[PDB]
Amino acid sequence: GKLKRVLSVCPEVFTMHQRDIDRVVKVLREKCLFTAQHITDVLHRCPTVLQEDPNELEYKFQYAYFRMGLTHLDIVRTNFLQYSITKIKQRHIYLERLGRYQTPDKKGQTQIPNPSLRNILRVSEAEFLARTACSSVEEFQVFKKLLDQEEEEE
Amino acid sequence: KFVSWKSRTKYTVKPVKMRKSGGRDHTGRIRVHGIGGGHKQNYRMIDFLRFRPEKEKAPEPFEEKVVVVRYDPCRSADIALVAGGSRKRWIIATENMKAGDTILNSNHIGRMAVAAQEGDAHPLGALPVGTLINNVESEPGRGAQYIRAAGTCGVLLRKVNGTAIIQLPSKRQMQVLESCTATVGRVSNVNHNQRVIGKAGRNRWLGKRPNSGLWKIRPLPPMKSYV
Amino acid sequence: RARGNEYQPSNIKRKHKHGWVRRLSTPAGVQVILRRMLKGRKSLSH
Amino acid sequence: AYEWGVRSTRKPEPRPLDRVYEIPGLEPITYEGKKHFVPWLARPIFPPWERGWNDPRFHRAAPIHEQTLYKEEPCYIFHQRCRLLEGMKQALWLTKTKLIEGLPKKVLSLVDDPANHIENQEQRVLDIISHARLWHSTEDIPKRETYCPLIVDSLIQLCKSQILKHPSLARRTSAQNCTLATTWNRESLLLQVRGTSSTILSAKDPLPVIASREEVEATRSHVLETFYPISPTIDLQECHVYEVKDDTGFQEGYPYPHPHTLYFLEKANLRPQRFLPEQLRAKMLLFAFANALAQARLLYGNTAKVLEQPIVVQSVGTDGRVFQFLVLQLNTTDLASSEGVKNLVWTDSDQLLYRHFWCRPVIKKKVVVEPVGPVDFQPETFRKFLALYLHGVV
RNA sequence: GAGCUACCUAAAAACAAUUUUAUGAAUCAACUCGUCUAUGUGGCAAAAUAGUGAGAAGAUUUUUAGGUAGAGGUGAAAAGCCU
RNA sequence: CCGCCUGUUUACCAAAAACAUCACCUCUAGCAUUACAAGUAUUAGAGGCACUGCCUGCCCAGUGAUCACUUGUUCCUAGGGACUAGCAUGACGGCUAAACGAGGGUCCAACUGU
RNA sequence: AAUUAUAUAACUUAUCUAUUUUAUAGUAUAAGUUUGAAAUUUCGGUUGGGGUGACC
Ligand SMILES: [Mg+2]
Ligand SMILES: [Mg+2]
Ligand SMILES: [Mg+2]
Ligand SMILES: [Mg+2]
Ligand SMILES: [Mg+2]
Ligand SMILES: [Mg+2]
Ligand SMILES: [Mg+2]
Ligand SMILES: [Mg+2]
Ligand SMILES: [Mg+2]
Ligand SMILES: [Mg+2]
Ligand SMILES: [Mg+2]
Ligand SMILES: [Mg+2]
Ligand SMILES: [Mg+2]
Ligand SMILES: [Mg+2]
Ligand SMILES: [Mg+2]
Ligand SMILES: [Mg+2]
Ligand SMILES: [Mg+2]
Ligand SMILES: [Mg+2]
Ligand SMILES: [Mg+2]
Ligand SMILES: [Mg+2]
Ligand SMILES: [Mg+2]
């Protein structure tokens, strides 16, 4: 069954050259320190990762590992990699500036309970703003444009 | 100065004396830690090519008689002495082998499936799909190398053309030609894992030395701040 | 424990470790003999 | 298929020949003239060496195929160490014989008469056991390689004392370590026996026949059992360089031409080196049968036929504690076919003279549980031993 | 340079009496180790003596020969040991 | 009080609460002629850690309820398709358990030139 | 920490063979890139000795 889902989502897995497949796997192992079983889990769960080039997958993983403070198991369980970087930064940064999110400290503790990752990403934007952040739709649109300008300057 | 003890050139059923290593190479330096001592042991040569026709005999299926089922110090499974014609040889013993039984070694890829009794050796093609097997051979005529441990069995998942898919105990699937022999049934000593060592002295008997007393994701430049 | 007694004599060990046949077995040992011959030693080996 | 013998232990391959040899027309310069090896000259090639005369201490045997007695057809030889996998069943097939359990009635009756009883028989037997196991040595516990031979010689001496009653016992003698052999065929198989006897008792007169001609003929109904898939020749020694010989144990002209009993011992101290009971009995049949056949062939030539006068031979075997008795009658010499008149054998198995012996008293809490000496002595076994000895006189 | 010491290979060896049982059990010699105190401090001794203590059929102790060498070896890790 | 227990360690100032240890847990590996091993996933190597039972066990997509919407992820152009029904949480505490110790403390009796 | 790093591990381009109608296999070597087992070298000054500050 795992092959069936992979074939449907990513028909080119057979067509892709050897080099391309190895790099995606090698990044997950040497640079991301994923275990053997998780590697099979990720490939089956989100086949689109194979299409994605390296040096973008590594950045996305480190964004969660360091900036968001997530752990290996959390990433695998929630299908974090499936989502796009733009969505991750737009939502996470908005919450962080509002003070509703905290990077876990060195000890591993947080003064305030952080919002569940499903609420941050899985839910719709309307529910996410209305419930998780309790903000206004107009403010988010302004923030997205402001964030775009900052990236351009960067 | 180290000389390997594995120098005998002719097959026999007589026990052979073994020399221990200590975990040292032929140079004399430790290569593997945790090995040393134990009880003295004798080696009994096991023949893993089930379908070996006797000298000056044609290649057709033959039968053999089970003389003994015996404990072996060098393995987790138990072995059985089997005699046929004018020849005796050791082999591995399945779960339910008993003394005095007769067993069949076959060379015939039946166009239809051959009824399978535990312990008989048949080419993989003949056996029906889903039949447990052990002592599997990767290549025809090589000799068994997989699934020869105690209580372990494999499964014949599928057959297409002249190639079959086997499910190893680790569950990693594998494929081979259908012209390589295999023997039906699980390996003996199904309850090996249940043992309890009990005291430290028992491990020293088996030839195991104690452990030693002594007690990496690099962030990218944008990750340095929130490390 | 009391030290000073590390020499536990054994003729078989002595001749095998430092003897004539042992010295000639390697080129480094052969050069040991040549140095002692040039100095003039009365005892080339054990 | 796994190959036995790791490469590192095998002899190393010869050095490659110098490239100067490849070049045609060029004579290499070697160190042969110097008479010693040097690393910077070519290695000579020497022709094979011949001494020019024979030195006995450095004799070298010719290969098997060059031996004058090499024969393409194989001969299977049965000797002392051979241990038959199938036991008696295989032994019976090889000798074309039928088995009857229990000793012959005539022999058994010899000892039921109290006139044949020895004086103080039970007490004297107990003394022999104690002497064999404890008293004969200066050591605390003697070993089997000593007392197993000793018990048998002492018992023969006890029975041999009956010459006072029967003067006719002076017509037999005994020899030590005699050898026996025979060649015969079974269903196209060439078979030979090469063996030895611990002691052999020979008589001046043949033993009485056990079975009448009517019983001999009735054996034709019996069929020899088979043991497929195991071949009859399992555990026999296949030889391609052999000679055909027959040997009773003595050369022609011996005054005592009739062998009476054959004795076989299991004196090895270590258990794995000692035959098990069934395998001991199988050895006794073949060794005794060879003695009978060699005696027949001697009298009636090499022809095959049903014998007018059957030949009877006895055999006794022990490890020093357990005893086994055998009587054989040879009825026919035509063994090529598996159907016809069959030979007959009577066996009495696993007869215990004593169960156990203590060389030191067993003490628990300063109480002597077991005294020294034999345990559970059975006098019946000796009477069977005595009966066989007396047979042919009384 | 592994005749000391650390670990390993091969061939050998020792273990009384008593109570339990059926054993890395118990009491306690031989033997192995070294808790505590005093004497000694160019000492009998460059680590001992006198008492007193721990184990003592086991992961026990002991003998003979062989192996691993300094950018290294060995280590039931004390940064211990390798004349 | 500490450590489960018999064991081990700084030869020459430390013998212990340290090290090892049965038990339990994590990671890596589908294979032959010199170690692992003449072995093959109930196997081998590396590492962590007292055991035992006993509370605390939750990132399955939400609501309807095996069914419809709302989500999410994707494409083809705000429209149109594709995918998400071959599965389904977890993380602490107090526990100790009798036995055992030339381990560190407290106490009674007897005993004595302390 | 600075400076290197044919220890391994990967790739890439040549070179040399096979084939193939361009083409995929491999590779006694050279040049790059990625990992880093290791290698060589260093530890400014005044402020008591520190601890935060500073200062030249
Ligand atoms: Mg540790
Ligand atoms: Mg000195
Ligand atoms: Mg030594
Ligand atoms: Mg010594
Ligand atoms: Mg004792
Ligand atoms: Mg010590
Ligand atoms: Mg004690
Ligand atoms: Mg004690
Ligand atoms: Mg004890
Ligand atoms: Mg430490
Ligand atoms: Mg320290
Ligand atoms: Mg020194
Ligand atoms: Mg302790
Ligand atoms: Mg202790
Ligand atoms: Mg030690
Ligand atoms: Mg000290
Ligand atoms: Mg102590
Ligand atoms: Mg001390
Ligand atoms: Mg500890
Ligand atoms: Mg203590
Ligand atoms: Mg008081």
Image: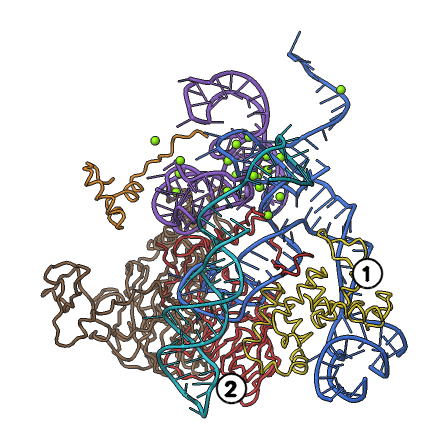
Chain colours: A yellow, B red, C orange, D brown, E purple, F blue, G cyan
Q: Nearer the viewer, residue B21 or A33?
A: A33
Q: Is residue B191 visible?
A: yes
Determine the image quadrant of residue E78: top right
Q: Amino acid at mark 1?
A: Leu
Q: Please identify the quadrant where the C terminus of chain A is shown.
A: bottom right
Q: Which residue is pictured at 25% across the width and 67% down the height? A: D14
Residue at which label 1 appears: A98
Badge 2 crowding class, 10 Å Cα cut-off, few under 14, some 14 to 19, many 20 or more, is some
- CA gap between label 2 and label 1 equals 74 Å
Q: Is residue D225 visible?
A: no
Contact, mark 2 vs mark 1 (Cβ under 8 Å): no
Residue at which label 2 appears: B109
Q: Amino acid at mark 2?
A: Ile
Q: Is residue B28 left or right of residue A7?
A: left
On the same chain, marks 2 and 1? The answer is no
- The number of discs equals 2
- Give residue C38's position: percent from left, percent from top: 19, 40
Q: Nearer the viewer, residue D91 or A131?
A: A131
Q: Please identify the quadrant where the N terminus of chain A is shown.
A: bottom right
